[PDB]
Amino acid sequence: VVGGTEAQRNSWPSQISLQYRSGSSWAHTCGGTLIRQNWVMTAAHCVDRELTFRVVVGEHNLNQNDGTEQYVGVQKIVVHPYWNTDDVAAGYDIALLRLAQSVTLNSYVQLGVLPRAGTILANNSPCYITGWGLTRTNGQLAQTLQQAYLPTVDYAICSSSSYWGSTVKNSMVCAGGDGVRSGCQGDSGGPLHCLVNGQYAVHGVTSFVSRLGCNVTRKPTVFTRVSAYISWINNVIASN
Ligand SMILES: [Ca+2]
Ligand SMILES: [Xe]
Image (cartoon, rainbow, N blue to C red; front, side):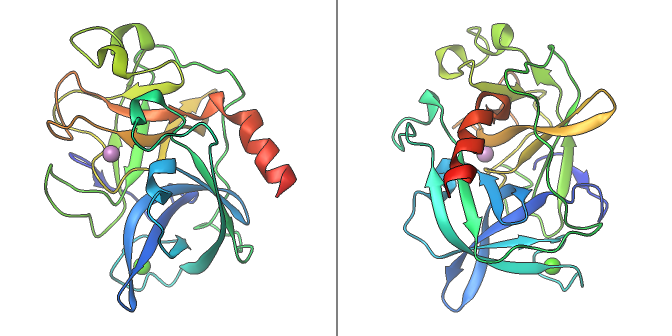
């Protein structure tokens, strides 16, 4: 996250770190949202590489003992059947991970609540992106969970020529684009949290930023629109 602030330890208890095996260590690659005690929602592009994955819940600092972490292997990966790795602009950038164990819920570990199906946020709806992604374009991962205030940019504006043009779809949510704050590499798969009727819900799964850089004016961060995938999600969990 570029231009973020450090999240308090208990603000975003559904945020997870998706990690892969590198040597005999694990390295953070992507964010995710805990949606069942044994299921995580992330971005399809995060799980294209044939890698060993683990999920960390109750994670705050990637390189320090928080005293709150649970570490759980990924047992099954279900990527959206329509996802095409060579065509992120087509959408469908979403995947579900079944965990090898069911995690224990507490103030640091909670299920993320999803919006009602078909819900579209009004232009300029206030949201926070969260994650451990790069803090600068071509920079380094954050050590501690970051959050940034990123207001939505509706489809009409986001798909206009100054913005993302034909690249963005109605299956996506754009947020931010002020040139100061944004998602960045390593935030992919993580949540966009938006307050609706007094409660946060996870409206986005972080998908992409400009190839020109993370925080680029009129290139808001783009997210898979969660409310487009409600029946897909439920169908996968009910059959697995
Ligand atoms: Ca930690
Ligand atoms: Xe990203």
